[PDB]
Length: 157
Image (cartoon, rainbow, N blue to C red; front, top):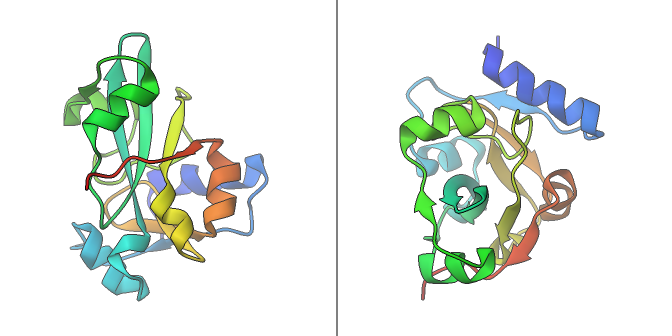
């Protein structure tokens, strides 16, 4: 049985029009992105991290490649100003879920979003579904249509 938080995410996919996609439960010890990757037999680069940063007029969601690291220099240029990495506590609210488990949809407070163009380098990806131990699969395209993010260059070199 999936958790309450995993249940919402799943319901959100269905009301938005992506009911064929599904949330799967992973081992209770699954804490990082590589353990998550091992579990579905995916490369660590296919995992999607939902990073929350706070700007002057609101929060922004950054969906980054598991093998990459967000370049704050680029992050600021896209937004159009300075950003503040959301504190793990602040994440609790702007979202309502756990840090290390933040879902790219099913939110209570919709945020603008950017998506690591390196994710389109794969046929399918795995985004978090509620907790560090939940994930759901989708093609780069579907995640783009689900979230409505702007594909962008975000990685450090």
